[PDB]
Image (cartoon, coloured by chain):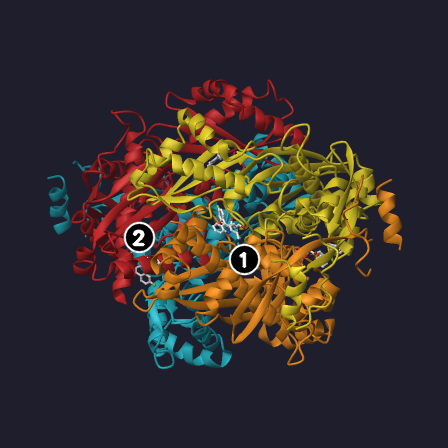
Chain colours: A yellow, B orange, C red, D cyan
Amino acid sequence: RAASIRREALQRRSIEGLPLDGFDYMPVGYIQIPVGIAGPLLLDGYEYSVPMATTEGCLVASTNRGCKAMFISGGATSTVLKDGMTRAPVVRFASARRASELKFFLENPENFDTLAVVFNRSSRFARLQSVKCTIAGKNAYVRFCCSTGDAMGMNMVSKGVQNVLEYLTDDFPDMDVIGISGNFCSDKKPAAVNWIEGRGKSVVCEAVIRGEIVNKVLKTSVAALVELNMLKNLAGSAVAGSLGGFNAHASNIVSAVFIATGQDPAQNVESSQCITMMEAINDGKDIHISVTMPSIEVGTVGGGTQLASQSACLNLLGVKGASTESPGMNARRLATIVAGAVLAGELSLMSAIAAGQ
Amino acid sequence: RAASIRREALQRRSIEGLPLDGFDYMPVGYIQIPVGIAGPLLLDGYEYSVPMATTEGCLVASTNRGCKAMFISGGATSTVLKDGMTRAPVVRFASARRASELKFFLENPENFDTLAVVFNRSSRFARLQSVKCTIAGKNAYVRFCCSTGDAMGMNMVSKGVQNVLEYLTDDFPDMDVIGISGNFCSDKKPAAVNWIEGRGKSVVCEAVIRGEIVNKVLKTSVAALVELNMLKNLAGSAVAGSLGGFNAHASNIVSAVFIATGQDPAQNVESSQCITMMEAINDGKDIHISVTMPSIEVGTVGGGTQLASQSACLNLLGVKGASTESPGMNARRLATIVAGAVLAGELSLMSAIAAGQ
Amino acid sequence: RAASIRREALQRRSIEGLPLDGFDYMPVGYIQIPVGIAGPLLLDGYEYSVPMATTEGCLVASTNRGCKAMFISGGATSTVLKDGMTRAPVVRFASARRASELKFFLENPENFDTLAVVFNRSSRFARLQSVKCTIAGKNAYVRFCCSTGDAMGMNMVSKGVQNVLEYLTDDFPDMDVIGISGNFCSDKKPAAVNWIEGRGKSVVCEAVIRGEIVNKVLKTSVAALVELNMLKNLAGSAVAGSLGGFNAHASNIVSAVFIATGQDPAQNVESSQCITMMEAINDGKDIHISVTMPSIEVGTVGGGTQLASQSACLNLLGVKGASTESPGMNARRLATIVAGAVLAGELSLMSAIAAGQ
Amino acid sequence: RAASIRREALQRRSIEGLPLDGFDYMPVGYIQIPVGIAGPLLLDGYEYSVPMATTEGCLVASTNRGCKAMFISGGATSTVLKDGMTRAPVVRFASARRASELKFFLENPENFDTLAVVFNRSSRFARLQSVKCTIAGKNAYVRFCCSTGDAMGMNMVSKGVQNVLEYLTDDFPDMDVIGISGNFCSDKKPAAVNWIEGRGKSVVCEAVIRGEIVNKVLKTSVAALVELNMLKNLAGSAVAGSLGGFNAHASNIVSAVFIATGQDPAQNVESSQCITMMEAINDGKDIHISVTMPSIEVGTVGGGTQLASQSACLNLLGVKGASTESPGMNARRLATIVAGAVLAGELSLMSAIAAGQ
Ligand SMILES: O=C(O)C[C@H](O)C[C@H](O)/C=C/c1c(C2CC2)nc2ccccc2c1-c1ccc(F)cc1
Ligand SMILES: O=C(O)C[C@H](O)C[C@H](O)/C=C/c1c(C2CC2)nc2ccccc2c1-c1ccc(F)cc1
Ligand SMILES: O=C(O)C[C@H](O)C[C@H](O)/C=C/c1c(C2CC2)nc2ccccc2c1-c1ccc(F)cc1
Ligand SMILES: O=C(O)C[C@H](O)C[C@H](O)/C=C/c1c(C2CC2)nc2ccccc2c1-c1ccc(F)cc1
C-alpha cells in the first residue's frame, strides 16, 4: 500500500522492471532470481532435488553433472564434526593481569554450569557449549559458543552474551564492555579463528568415483584429477596466500543454495570455507573425493527462511522449519546438503578442467 | 511453459510458495527478495538512492542512519585506485628453469604489445594491462590483468588467456596447460593476492564527521569511535587472524547491493574485502572515516544485470548498461556507490556499538 | 682431535678465522657471536641483565633505552596465559566417517585419563593437557598438547604421541600413521593454529609510561605513539597481510636472547609472534603499552642450554637448569623475560620512530 | 679491556662459562655455536661444503643424507627469479584523494628516472627497481625496491627512501612522514606482501631423484613421498592456516647457514618462507622435488659477515665479500646455496618420515 506510494516518490529515475505486486509485506519492491534444480544428490541414503537460486544457468547444469556422477558411484557420505554458533564481545580492564583473571575465571570448569544457566535464559533453545577468553594487552575477546536449535541464532547467542556480561559485574565491576562484537567471532568476515575453530556446522562430505566412471563418464583419469587438485586447489591456493580457499568454487554453490533457502547471503564469505581433497585409492584404480567445510552457517527457522518462495525451497529438501525429531536436526541436515552440492560442484568443474587437457 | 510442467514433475514434496508466473524465461520458478532504499548517499557530488536486496530490514535502516550522518557532514569522496579483472591459468614444464623462461619472456616489456594484440581479439572491450608469472617448482601461475568495459568480464579475460596460451605454443610447445584457472586469480575465494594486488575496482571512500554531529547525531564521541575502530576492526580482526576482514560488516552491504543490482553473489567473498580507518583530525575535534576495498568485482552489463528487476535497480543509480561517456565508467561508478554504502554501514553500526557503552 | 684432522681435510678453500680451540666437544669448529646486556629490565618485581647475542650493537643500545624508560615507570608486569608444547601427527583411514570416529573418541572426556596414562610414560615430566583431532577428508591431524617441565620438550611430546599412536591400534587397527608431524603443530613455521591456539608459553607483558616521561625522556607524546602503533603495527601489518606480525621488531629481540640462552634459533619464526598494543589512559595523560605473544617456545634444560657460554647467560637471568620450586618454572620465567625485553624493544624503536617526526 | 672490567661489574650472578678472550672487539663476552658441514651439495655445476652453525647435530647428518641422495641424482638446479631489497615508509595526507595523487605520481613511468637519480645517491651500489604506493584511508605505504650489490643493504635502501622523501616536499609539502617503516616492507615479520611480491632473492631449486635411488637409498617410493608432500606440506599447512609455511623444516637449515655465514638471524622468519613441491615424472618412475622461496634475505658484505669466524664460513662457499664478476653475484649465489641446502633438508626429513611408515 505505502510501499506502492513510496515507489512513485522515488521516480519523482525509472524503477519500472522492479515488481511491486506478488509479495506479501521500508520495502519499495522485490527482485526475482530464477531457481534451478541439481539432482538427484544421493546423500547419507536420501535423494535431494537441490534448489539453486542463480542467474548463471551453466552452474545448475555443472552441479547436475556432478550429482549424476556421484549417483552411479554410491552417492555421498556427510559427517557433522561440530555444531555451534559463536559471538565474541571485546571487554577491557585497566591491566592485562586483571583481564587474565576474567579469562582464568570463565575458563575454569567449575564456573561453567553457572555461566550456562545465566546464558540459557536467552531462549528455550540456547544451550551454551564453551567460552574461550583470548587476551590482547588489557582487552579480552570472549568467544561464546552455543547450540541454537534450527535458527541460525545470532540474536539468541547475543541475548546470552549480554546475560553473562551483566552477571559478570558482580565479580568484575571494573570491566568495560567496548563492543557486543570485537571481530573475534568472526561474523561475515574470513578469519583463521573460523577455519581452525569452526563456526556453525563443521561438515565433511565424501564419495568414491571408480576408475571406470572417471574414464567413461568424466572423460579424464584418477591421476589427472589427483594432480589438478594438488596444483590448483592446494599449491595454487597456497601460492595465492589463501585462507580457507583450498577449493575450486564452493562459493558459487553455497551462494546459490543460500539465496534459494533464504539464508543470510553475507554469511557466504565464511560458509564457502572449504578444503577439497582428491586421493587415489585401491592401487590407484579409484578416487576418494571430499570437501571439509568448518563454518557452514544456516538455519531452517527465522530470517528469510519463512518467506513464501524460500520456504518452498527448504520444503523441497524436507528441512523446512524446526525439527520434530529434535531441535537442530533440520539445520544440521541443510548443512550436509550444502556440503554434498559443493562436493558435486567441485567434482563437475574439477573434471571439466582436467578433461579439457 | 516447460518449466511449468517441470514443477509438477518434482511434486510427483510441495514447492507451492515458489512463484512461477511473473518472470520472462532449466528454470523451475524464481525466489523473491524485498528491496529497501538507503539514501540520500551524497557521493562525489551526486545523490543516490542505494537499492539493497535483503530480508533483515534493520540493515536498510542502519545504512540509512549512516547516509544521513554523512549527508549533513559534506558527503563522501571516493577515489578509484586501480581497475582491472584477472584470470591466472596454471601451466607447467619439465623444469623450474624452463618455467622461469616463460616468466622472464612474458614479463619482458618488449614482448607486451604482441601479447596485448593477441589477448585483445577476445573482444572490442578487452584491453590487457599486465601479466605476472609466479613460479612454484616447475609450475607457472600467469596472472593476466585487463580492462573489460562495463562487463565484469570473466569470459572476456578467459577468451584472452586462451589467445595468448595458443600463441605461446610457437615459443613454448613443451608447456602443459594444467588449468584455465590455478586459484592464483583468486576467483570467489579470499586470497592475499587480491588484498595485496587488487582484483576488479580497487576503491577508497572517505568522509569527515564533525565533533558536533558525532555528539549531537551519533550520540558518541570522536575518541570513543577511533578507539572502538582500533580494538574491533584492527586489533580484533588481527587477534582472529583475519585476511581482508579489517571492518565491521562490509559483507552485509556489498551482498545487499550485489543481489539488487544483479551482480554474482559468490564474488561477495572478495568484494567484501575492506580496511575501515577512523582517525581523529583538527586537534581531536573531528573524525576522518574511510573504507579501503581492493577487490570490488562488478559490471553494469551482462549476467543478471539485464533481468527486468535488477536492471531497474541499476537504473535508479543511473549506471544501467554500458557507459556513453566511455566504456567502464558505469562499472567504476557502481563500485564507488558500493564503497560509499559500505562507509555509511560502517559509520552507522560502529556508532551504534560505541554509543551503546 | 678428529674435528682438528677434519678441518685440514676441507682445506685440501681456507677456513682460517673459524676457531677450533676454545670449545669442549661431526664438529669442524665453532663461530663466535658477541653478547651485549640490556638492563636493568624491571619485571614482576625482579631486575634482570638481559643477555643479547647479536652483531648489530645498536640493537643492545635500543633495548637498553627501553628498559630504562620502563625502570623509572614502575617496570613491566608479565602474565603467563597458557603453557604447553604441541606435536600433531597426520593419520588416515579409508573414510572421513571412520576418521571422525577417532576424533569423537580422542575428544571424549571419559577417554582422557587413559590417553594421559599412556602418553605420560614419555618421561617423569610429560603431563598431557589435551588432544584436538582436526579432520580433512579421510585424514586426521591430532594436536597433542602437554607440559614438559623446563625442557622445550619436543622429543618428550613425540615419545608420548608414539605411545598413544601404538595404544590406538587396539581400537583403530585400520589407522595409517602417515607422519609423526603433519605441519598442524606447526613447528618452525608461521601458522594460524599457533596464533589462535598458542604453542609453548603464551605471555602478555605490560607497563604504563607517564606523560611526563613520554615527553621528557622519549622526546614524543602519548598521542603520537598511540597513532604510530595503529598506523604501523596494526593498519600497516594488516595492509601487508601479516599473520602474527602486529609489532615493530619482536624478532630482533627474541633472536638475540634465543641465541645467547642456547634456544633453537629456527623456533624464532613462531616465538617472534606478537601483537603490540599502545593505549592512552588517565584522560590521555599516560600510555599503557603491551606485547601479547601466543607461542614463545623456550627451555632452560637440554639442547644448546647446557653449553658453557649459553649456560652462563641463563645463569645471569637465574633460570639456568630445572626449577627447584617446581618443574617448568624456570622455562616460564625465561618466556616472561623474553616478553619483557620485547616490550622494551617495541617502546625504544616505536619512540625513536615517533620522536623522529 | 673495558668489556673485561664490565664483566666483573655484572658478577658484583656468575657468567663464568661465557668466554671473553678469543674475539677481537658494549660487548661483555661472546657465545660459541659449533659448525657442522653438509656436502658435497652439487648445485648448478659446483660442489659446496655447506657450513651449518647448530647445537642439534642430527640436523647436519640429516642435511648430509639429502646432499648425497642429490649428488648421485645429478645434483640441484637453482634459478634466481627476482633480486631486490624493500623498505616501505607510511606517509599521510589530510585525504585519501590527496594520498592517491602521491600514488599515481610515484607510479607514473615518466617520473621513474628522476626518483631513481634521487634514490641512487644512497650509495655506489643502490639501483632503484620500482615503487609500489598502497593507499589505506589517507595513509600511503610506499614500497621501494632496489638492488644493493653484495650487502643485504637495509641502511642503503633507507638512505634512498629519505632521499626521495625529502625530494617529495617540493610537490607534496602537505605530506607527513609517520614512519621510515610502516610494516608493509615487511621486515623480520611473516607477511603476504613478501610471499606474493618477494623480498631480497626469490629462488627456485630443483632435483630429480630416480625410482631406483628412492627405493635403494631413501628406503621409500616415489608415490609415498608425493603423497606425504601433499598431506603434510600442502593440505597439512593449509588446515593449520599457514602463510609461506608449505614445507617441512626450511627454518632449521636457513637458521643454521644464516648463523654460520653471519646473516641477521631475525630475517630467518621471512627467509624460511618456502613451498616444497614433489611431483611424479616419467610415468611415475621418478620424482621431481623443488623448494620455491620468495624472500631469502642475505649479504656477503657488512654486518656479521666480516667477523673472523663467519667470514671463514662464507669463504668455504667461495662467496666471501663483494663480487669481482659484478656486484650482487656473491649474495645471489649464497641465496641459491641456501635454497639447495633447504632442498636437501626437505628430501632427507621427508624420506625419513615416509620411510618410517
Ligand atoms: O576456476 C576457478 O578458480 C573458479 C571459477 O572461476 C568460478 C566460475 O564460476 C566457474 C566457471 C566455469 C564453469 C561454471 C559452471 C560453474 N563451468 C565450466 C565448465 C567447463 C570448463 C570451464 C568452466 C568454468 C571456468 C571457465 C574459465 C575459467 F578460467 C575457470 C572456470
Ligand atoms: O559486529 C560484527 O562483527 C558484524 C555483525 O555481526 C553483522 C550483523 O549483521 C549486524 C548486526 C547489528 C545490526 C544490523 C543492522 C545491521 N544493527 C545493530 C544496531 C545497534 C546495535 C547492534 C547492531 C547489530 C549487532 C548486534 C549484535 C552484535 F553482537 C553485533 C552487531
Ligand atoms: O621498522 C621495522 O619495520 C623493523 C626494523 O626494520 C628492524 C630493524 O632491525 C631496526 C632498525 C632500527 C634500529 C635498530 C636498533 C634496532 N634503531 C633505530 C633507531 C632510531 C631510528 C630508526 C631505527 C631503526 C630503523 C631504521 C630504518 C627503518 F626503516 C626502520 C627502523
Ligand atoms: O616435522 C616437522 O613439522 C618439522 C620438525 O619438527 C623440525 C625438527 O627439527 C626435525 C626433527 C627430526 C629430525 C631432525 C634432523 C632435523 N630428524 C628426523 C629423522 C628421522 C625421523 C624424524 C626426524 C625428526 C622429527 C621427529 C619427530 C617429529 F614429530 C617430526 C620430525
Q: Is mark 2 within 8 Å of ligand 3?
A: no
Is residue C1 at least partly visible in the picture?
no
Specify whether C310 is left or right of D36: left
The percent position of residue A255, horizontal first and vertical second, equals 67, 51
The percent position of residue D143, horizontal first and vertical second, equals 43, 66
The percent position of residue C92, horizontal first and vertical second, equals 62, 31
The image quarter in which residue D131 lies: bottom left
Residue under pointer 2: C279
Locate the C terminus of chain D and report the quarter of the image it occupies: top right
Q: Nearer the viewer, residue A322 or A108?
A: A322
Q: Residue at x 36, y 31 (%)?
A: A105
Please give the count of numbered marks on the rendered protein: 2
Q: Nearer the viewer, residue B224 or C166?
A: B224
Chain of the residue under the numbered disc 1 shown in the image: B
Helix, strand or loop status at disc 2: strand
The percent position of residue C33, horizontal first and vertical second, equals 28, 48
Q: Nearer the viewer, residue A244 or B269?
A: B269
Q: Is mark 1 within 8 Å of ligand 2?
A: yes
Which amino acid is tagged 1? Ala
Q: In the rendered view, tell whether residue C117 sits above or below residue B221.
A: above
Chain of the residue under the numbered disc 2 shown in the image: C
Specify whether B218 is left or right of B61: left
Q: Residues within 10 Å of mark 2 (few under 14, many from 20)?
A: many
Specify whether B199 is left or right of D135: right
Residue under pointer 1: B61
